[PDB]
Image (cartoon, rainbow over all chains, first blue to last red; front, side, top):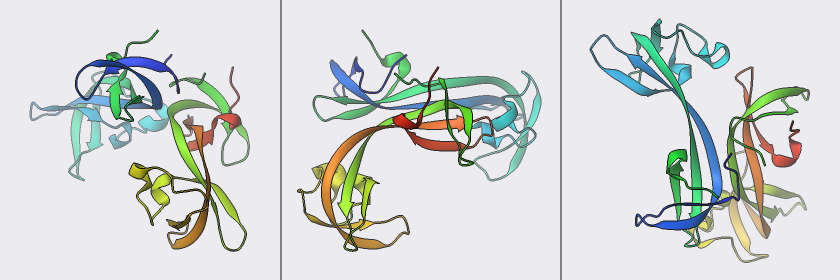
Length: 109
Length: 109
């Protein structure tokens, strides 16, 4: 429930705790996929799945075999593992300083 | 009091009303500029100003002549009028389509 203009406390650019204001917010949904190489990715944007229109239908079955477009520009096969949505925020200290801070790093009243 | 993930209603580009999800939010600085033909704009972002790096030094002096980049991609002279902060939100319909919306255009539950 963190909102625009809300005053929170988070770590500085110096690594110290100060009150700052929330001036931005974003929701990012990322997929975890397992390649055959034994490798994986966890910052796969949903639109990159080409064997299923996840933007509309939502994420595949856990363990589902999928095809995706990779940072390659090319298409590969993989196993969909998990889906995770994260909240990220932009804060502004009394500094004038700004930083991009993860929801988990923010203390609120 | 609008939050990431919250389901709201707004007009899509069809001009009709649909449920959408808030996936973004920003506290956005908007410049008002006055064109020579007598027209205005009030949703001009600070980076659009070409005759000064407003992202760092802040807004130009009031009434100041500025060169800006417009929605057609070309550069024009304009008269900086005032500066304003507005809450804007990024929403996503079940389409998968998205829209950038002012807080005032949003109906909430």
